[PDB]
Image (tube, rainbow, N blue to C red; front, side, top):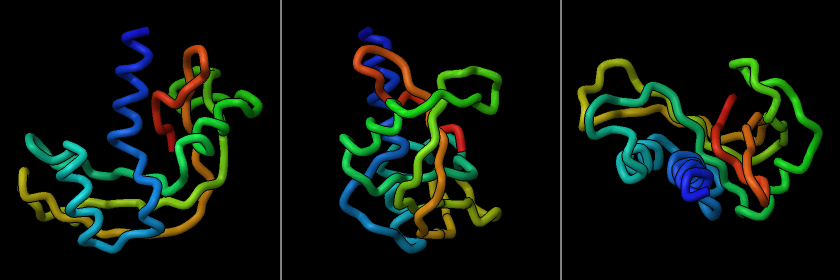
Length: 122
């Protein structure tokens, strides 16, 4: 579980920022860069979750549902987010985004002991 921890750390990096509440375009531009999703190509869509890690991890403890890829280790919850969508023009590593802040249903996959988030499904 050096593995499960690496996967969890990747989830935190790509998807977790507790104390923003809901960013604008500049927030997406900064965070996509700082969380390492722009150096080699521009990731087209990404979500940052604005909840405490304890609360995100709690989603793992809910009833299992199917992931998009067919796995059965997914879980749904409702959280504050900023969704970041690439503008379509941009050229890595200078990637540009449009932000949408909202509270919405998310689906995450969890693994391990304790169960932790390892993938953001939708």
